[PDB]
Each structure stands twice: as C-alpha cells, then as structure tokens.
Length: 19
Length: 353
Ligand SMILES: C[C@H]1CNCCCN1S(=O)(=O)c1cccc2cnccc12
Image 1 (tube, rainbow over the protein chains, first blue to last red):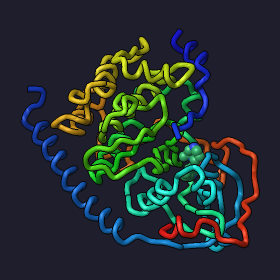
Image 2 (cartoon, helix red, strand yellow):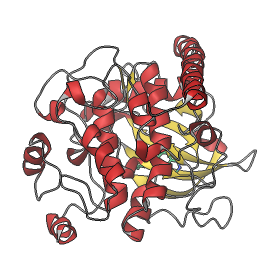
Image 3 (cartoon, each protein chain N blue to C red):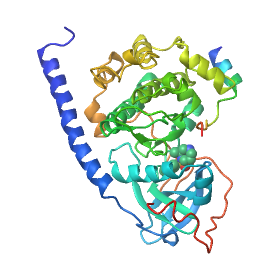
C-alpha cells in the first residue's frame, strides 16, 4: 500500500530542512 | 451564476474588508519593523525547566519567569555555532520578524536578550505540542480537522504575504497546537521579505515547490504549494511525495503527477490539484484572484473565515493539559547545561540582536 511505501521510505520522523 | 445577490454581495464585502484589514496591518508592521525593541530581560530572570525541542540552532526550553511565575519557551542559540553554520542573517532576521508581526496564529516574542555566549528569544509557551506528533499518533486527520488547521494557515499566509513575507518552511514539525486547539507558527529563520522574486535553495525536501528544486527565481507561490503538501499530509497521514532519498522526492515533485487516497473527497482532490500545480501560471494563490481562489474553493465552503480569525470556532481536538508548565505533549531530550563564558563571543556579528 501507499502507507507501507511511506513506512519503507524511512522518512516518517521529524524532517530536517536542507541547511 | 454560483451566487445569488445576497451571497455575492456578502462575499464581495468580506473580500473588501480583508483588504482594509491588511492595509492597516501592513502600516502597523512597517512601524514596528522600523522602530523595534531589544534587550528586554536577562537569563537569571528565569528558571530553566526542560528542553522542549532541539536543532542545529540550539534548543528550546520551557522556562518559568521568577518574578511573575509565567511559563515561556526560551530559544537558546550559541553564537559561535550560528556563525559556523552561516546563520547570522537568518537569526537576526527571525528576531526582527517576530518583533514586528502580530497575528493570532503567529507565536509572540515576549523577550529577547544576549550574553557572552548565547542569543535568547523568549516566546509564548505553546503547550499542545507539535502537530507532527499528533498526526503521527492519530494517523491522519479527518477532512474537517485538517480543514480547521488549513484555514488558519491560509489566513496566516494571507497576512504574511500582504507584508511581502515569504514563509518557506511550512511542515507539521513547525506547527504547534495551543491550549484551545489552534495553531501557532514559530520558526521564521527562512522567512524573507520578498516583494518580487528570490533564489535561495531552502526548505524541507517533501515540502519544496518544483521551482525551488529547479533553481528558478521564485515567489510567494511556493508557500501555497507547501500548503497543498500540508493539507495532503494532514488528510492522508503521509505527504504526496516521498522516497528513500531527497533526489527521488524531487523527481516526483517536479513530475506533475500526484496520487490520492481513495478516502479523499473530490473537493479535496480538486483543491490539491490546484495547489500542487507545477505550472506557476495555474497555481492557486498565484492567479489574478489571489488568495480568494483558495478561500472560495468548495472544500472551504463550510469555513467561516472571520470566526476562525476570531478563534470562535470549536477546535476538533484539544490537547491534554494538566496545568501551566505541563510538558507532556513534547518529547524528552537529553538536557545539557547552558555555559556562558567570561569572554564575549561574536560581538560584532550580533550587534543588532
Ligand atoms: C517549533 C518546534 C520545531 N522543532 C524544532 C525545535 C523548535 N520547536 S519547539 O521546541 O516545539 C518550539 C519552538 C518555538 C516556540 C515554542 C513554544 N512553545 C513550545 C515549543 C516551541
């Protein structure tokens, strides 16, 4: 599922800005 | 047409009143921007209680003002680190913006001061925690719940953009929930006064507009793109564009393709297709009718914009609140002493702070 794909991305936590 | 006489007149009048409000708010902002404030307290006026959040900037701590007993959120920046990370201008600009703006969903700066080692911004304590935490915990927000938050961001951006401020770092991580369930926007390090265009690569990968990724000159329309990302993430529980690595996210963002959960309403999908529009000439918020294309969209038909502004709408979610200084809606962080130093650091660079 798309949710499963989201979990697989590893980007479920707090995301830093580019800097 | 879509509106009869009474509804059309009411909407026209409402839109004119917004213009009148914004003109006054611009006047008030420019007065404060030109004649700011400074050095309004000192460190030993507060007890430091607990770290509420961290970053490369430094940390934000819950503090209690000794003389009054009021709790605040104190952002502590290490001057030497700010200089090493090339954030001098951003830090000075954040304080200048916070000192000058006034809006019910923008956090209020209550004090600021500096010492040999650190800069201090003492803001209202917003006890409900990060939207991010609530979203990951609940999973997703219902469309009415998402809409309530989205409306506050629309109004906040309408306000900021009237001041020629582009925000540039919208995401659930940067949105706090106050005791009444309303949103507070806090971080202005990447905000910029931009009447025309600007060029800096900055923001968070999932929330970057295509024109930023593609190294174009860009304008306030990047905030409306980011609103689309936020609404999508609030209502889906995950953002529209994700991948293992940022470059793959960027490929998806610029592609012009977005997919929606089957539970999204058609109204929501239509709004999001118009916000997540790669073509600037077609993106809502960037057309001749400006913010009204968003505020008048069907997905917002039930939104009483004035009642949201007046904070008279009952919030869909009220965070747990055990009392002043309750930090339960924030995570736990390793606590580190704040060392000053007998030697002033980076005095020249931060003279204006
Ligand atoms: C905005 C977030 C973003 N994540 C990185 C750390 C900063 N914080 S914070 O610590 O929750 C925070 C910042 C500013 C003012 C606040 C007022 N009350 C409570 C927390 C506050």
